[PDB]
Every structure is written in structure tokens, then in C-alpha cells.
Image (spheres, rainbow, N blue to C red):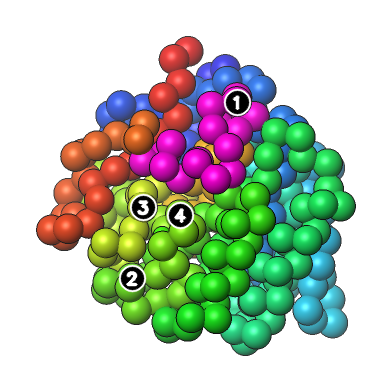
Amino acid sequence: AAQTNAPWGLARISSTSPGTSTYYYDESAGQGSCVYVIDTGIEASHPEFEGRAQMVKTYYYSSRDGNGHGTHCAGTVGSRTYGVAKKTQLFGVKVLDDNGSGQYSTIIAGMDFVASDKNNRNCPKGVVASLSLGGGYSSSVNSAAARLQSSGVMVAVAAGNNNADARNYSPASEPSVCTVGASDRYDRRSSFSNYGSVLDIFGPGTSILSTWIGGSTRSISGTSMATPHVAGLAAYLMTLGKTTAASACRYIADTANKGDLSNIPFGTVNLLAYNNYQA
Ligand SMILES: [Ca+2]
């Protein structure tokens, strides 16, 4: 399949080189997979989700996304125009309030929720979780991310936006999950992207167009935006039968564009997520 004039990040993920604008992907499109977006929520009613998004949990007085952040992320995962996995099922878990904030304790609870909740969902091709959030190092937060992963969910997390070593952030520093740095359309490490040995992969994160609340769209930037590209990619690859929740991060690293990014600090992987799709 070919989507012309796609957001640059979608095009980049199906390309061996920067500077193209068409997104190429197998039409299976992540059908039969599920992605949990653990964030400010999802405006499920957005036309771009086509009935494939649902709120499953909130820790606040509402499950609506009163921010837009969770909605943007979900859109990059699986909206029809702005999504990597255009046919995946999207499940929203509101651990972050409408200011985008959340106590670590609620975030942990949300991770443990998904690990159980996938047993109440129909996801024959596999389960992915996209965590575009983080804070300072916490062993409890990392442990929760490690449980979610061990349970059979492909866990993708943001490296963080401090232009700093991600070892000092959680869940970014957890070894057993997929930690995702950000790049721009010229293949530079995004100026705010964290780095370090704990990163597993980079995805598009600068100037990323996706869905927003009020049924609109906008371009914003962050390792928050890179993460859902990798999450959507994993879901897509799982439906293709190429990989599984336990091996998807490795598989993506293995099949990545390699050595192509600039301003990657010494000791950080130079790998850009790539679907290796041959149209
Ligand atoms: Ca990691």
C-alpha cells in the first residue's frame, strides 16, 4: 500500500533515505493487533480513529483527553491518515491528567492494568504498549515497565526530552523495554532527545503531524512522538508475523536503518526504525 503526501515520519519509517513523502506499508496494517496508549487519554470519537479507538481505564474523574497529548500519540500509532498501523485496535489508559501530569503511583497502576487487561481484549496478532511519559529514575516505575513487558506486551517508552543520558529517567532506563529517542526530518538527533546506552532505537519525533482533541490536528515534537512510531511499527510487524512482543524491540533494532543519524553521542545506538517494506 502507498499513502502519498504522508507525514514525513511515516514516510521515513518506510524508507532507506530521508527526504521522501510517501508512506509504504503492507495493507494488513496491524489488523488483529492492539496498542495501549498510556497517557492523557484518547479522543476516541475523532473521525481519524474510525471506531477503532476506545478508552478502557482512567484514574481521574473523567476518561476524556482534556489535553490532546494522548490523542496525538494514539494518532501516530493508528489513525487512518497519521498512523503507522492504520488497522490496529487502540486502547486508552488515562494515567496522566489534563495538565499532562501523573503521580508515579498512578502510572505504575496503569502499567499493571494493561498487563491484566490484555486478557480482556481480542488481540490475536499481539499486544503493544506506548508510554510517552517519564520522570526521574525510579526502580518501582522501571519494575512496573518490566512486568508489563514480561507479561507479553511489547513495551515502547520515550527516552525523555532533556538532551541528557536516559539512564537517569524512568521508565526510559529500564533495560527490558524498548526505549525510543527522537530524530528530525533531516536525520539529525532531535535537539531535545535523550541519549545513552539504555536507548534501543530512534523514531521520528520533530515536527510530527497527528490528531488532536476537538477533532483536529497539529504538529508537535518530543520523544513522546517518536515512541508511538515504534509502537505502531511493532504492532504492524506483529500482524505480519515477523516478530512477537518479546522480540519486537530486538527485531526493530536488527532491521533498522543503521549509521544514518547525525549528532548521535558516542556509545548511543545509531538505528532508525524502518519497516523494511518492499512494495
Ligand atoms: Ca530500554
Residue denoted by label 3:
200
Q: Earlier in the sequence, mark 4 or mark 2?
A: 2
Disc 4: which residue = 178
- Taking 46 as reference, is 130 left or right? left
Say which mark, if any, is on residue 241.
1
Q: Position of residue 191 (x, y in %)?
A: 26, 63
Q: CA distance from mark 4 to mark 3?
A: 6 Å
Residue hosting label 2: 166
The single residue placed furthest to the front in the displayed view is 150
Magenta segment range? Answer: 236-253
Check disc 1: other Cα within 10 Å, few if <14, some if 14-19, many if 20+: few
> Are the residues flagged by discs 4 and 3 in contact, CB closer than 8 Å?
yes
Q: Residue at coordinates 28% horizontally, 29% vertically from top-left?
A: 17
Label 1 vs 4, first from the N-terminus: 4
Q: Is residue 165 above or below residue 227?
A: below
Distance, label 2 to label 1, CA atoms, is 31 Å
